[PDB]
Amino acid sequence: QIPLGIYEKALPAGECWLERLQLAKTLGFDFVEMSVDETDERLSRLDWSREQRLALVNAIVETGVRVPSMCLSAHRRFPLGSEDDAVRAQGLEIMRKAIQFAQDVGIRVIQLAGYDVYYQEANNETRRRFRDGLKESVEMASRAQVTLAMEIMDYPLMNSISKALGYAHYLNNPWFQLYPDIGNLSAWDNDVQMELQAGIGHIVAVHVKDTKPGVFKNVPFGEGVVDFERCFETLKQSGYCGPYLIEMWSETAEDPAAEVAKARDWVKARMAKAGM
Amino acid sequence: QIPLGIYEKALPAGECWLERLQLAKTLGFDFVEMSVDETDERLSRLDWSREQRLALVNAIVETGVRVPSMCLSAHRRFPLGSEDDAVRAQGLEIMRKAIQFAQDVGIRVIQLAGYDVYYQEANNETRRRFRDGLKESVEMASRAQVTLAMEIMDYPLMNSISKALGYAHYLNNPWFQLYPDIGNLSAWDNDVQMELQAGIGHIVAVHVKDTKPGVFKNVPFGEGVVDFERCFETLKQSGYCGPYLIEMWSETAEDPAAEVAKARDWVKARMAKAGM
Ligand SMILES: [Zn+2]
Ligand SMILES: [Zn+2]
Ligand SMILES: [Zn+2]
Ligand SMILES: [Zn+2]
């Protein structure tokens, strides 16, 4: 049966994980994806004590709701391509800490953000520094035996499965894999269905959200350009058996749980249509 | 860093995992590989309670000594190729329970036994049943996001990297990888150094021991046909950045602790001559 998860930032903001995990179970999800983003509050998770780490493991084992993956979007703030050597070193230290964290709490996959730089302008130097930082991250990941899976991004350097496969070929490492976002993939000039089929033996997780050209965030399900039934059809037929994660940001909604319930039923209807 | 690890059965027996991990720490090992073999005793680990599983996580985090991998030799007794449907079901159940155990406890890689059958003679039907059992196993691993790694075996069906690569290509799944034993890879008529280069983007871990033509188990370090310095050179030059696990049964043989320290330094000496 198909594992279905919810993004952390879809649910109420608390740092009590047992409550967060119990809520996910109640809403019918098998898992939660943790965000380690640009904010200092989530960034501080990497400096958690042994007891804070073991408390998360406790809540997981007790509720049965897994935290198999981490979204590492902190690299938008501290990119690995930064020609500011201080910022780049901060980005690699965050990579090191996310992997140790992953080891500590049994996170299966760290989703990488494919930005060479975000708030600054890319050039050849940012692309070379990003590539080297990726090799270095993947080396750390080989030692720890932790999967780093590159997201297909809201950003041209990594805006297709083909571009992620380029990096995968260059790296040639079993611990570097693919985590496509079917929304991000659908908002450029890609052949989406061929891209999905092309990545198959590299795809470890799928992000599920709607988008429009140039709009990658908070676009409501059904109001964008993503052909969900087609994407699930292709993935199923091509032999994909991994998890799907509903990505939304309803932490700011009046009733986060009610929004998540509606999004879950909407996504599930389309999975069912496509044979799953 | 080269992560160096020690097989469970190279250390004194029992179920206090805290003491064992502590022992491996003072001996200078980064990690311990757990065994889930043919004994009811070790199989009952798959039936541990949430509390037993948590106590193991606690000890790992306390000591800093990881348990990143599991040797799953239990399939010799309950093979996936068995023409006895009841024996086959048991092996599949074991596979399922091992994946969940790996989830609960944060094990990175489950090392699979590459035998269609072991105590019976193989035929087209056992090969077929083993093939479909593997596929079922890999689908379970994809949902859970747990790596299953095929060991290079003391058995003709999987006696090279090439054989494991054949299965890897057939399965075309990121959760099926490769776990070469350089002893077993050397105990046949293989081109060893070619094999290790061939498998490189699939190799997640490496078993280190010594063997002879025909003889597979416990030949002391240096007395077999394994060219350690050359194997370590091939892997170093090819871009391997993963762990090495020293396979020993010291738990029997004289002063177990003093034997693993000799073999630890013997392995490290061979690695250092190879550029490492
Ligand atoms: Zn490929
Ligand atoms: Zn996404
Ligand atoms: Zn291959
Ligand atoms: Zn071995």
Image (cartoon, coloured by chain):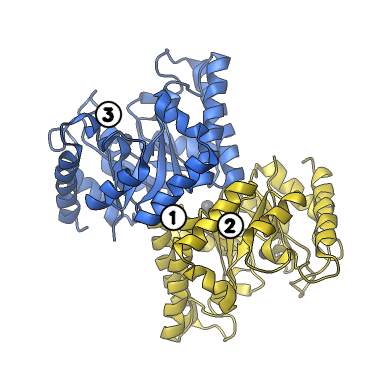
Chain colours: A blue, B yellow
Task: Give the camera-side residue of B176 and A220.
Answer: A220
* Classed neighbour count for the residue bearing mark 3: other residues with Cα under 10 Å, few (<14), some (14–19), many (≥20): some
Residue found 29% across the figure and 34% down from its top = A9
Task: Give the camera-side residue of B198 and A247.
Answer: A247
Task: Give the camera-side residue of A186 and B105.
Answer: B105
Q: Position of residue A195 (x, y in %)?
A: 33, 41
* In the image, residue B224 above or below residue B24: below
Quadrant of res A198:
top left
Residue found 23% across the figure and 52% down from its top = A26
* Classed neighbour count for the residue bearing mark 1: other residues with Cα under 10 Å, few (<14), some (14–19), many (≥20): many
Residue found 54% across the figure and 53% down from its top = B57
Q: Chain of mark 3?
A: A
Judging by the rendered image, the residue that carries numbered circle 3 is A188
Q: Quadrant of ligand 2?
A: top left
Quadrant of res A33:
top left
The amino acid sitting under disc 1 is: Asn
Judging by the rendered image, the residue that carries numbered circle 2 is B69
Marks 3 and 1 share the same chain: no
Q: Chain of mark 2?
A: B
Judging by the rendered image, the residue that carries numbered circle 1 is B173
